[PDB]
Length: 104
Image (cartoon, rainbow, N blue to C red):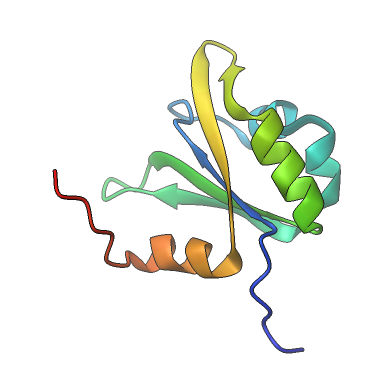
């Protein structure tokens, strides 16, 4: 099956320190029900602990958009997690640590 770049991926950002797998599912709500098999990838930092970034690939791009809209800076317990939709390419790009231009 050819890897198709669909915008079915979502980047969560600002996740709590040690937000658990069920905790993140709660946060997702019903959107966790349409997640692709092992679609949830948490980004770890040097220490081997979450960067606060996570990428979740859902089955459907429409659901991903809906989730990214629903959770675009949503209050997760006591934190605000800003969720943004992404493509498979964007997901890999951030995971690979692609060149992101920010003159700051």
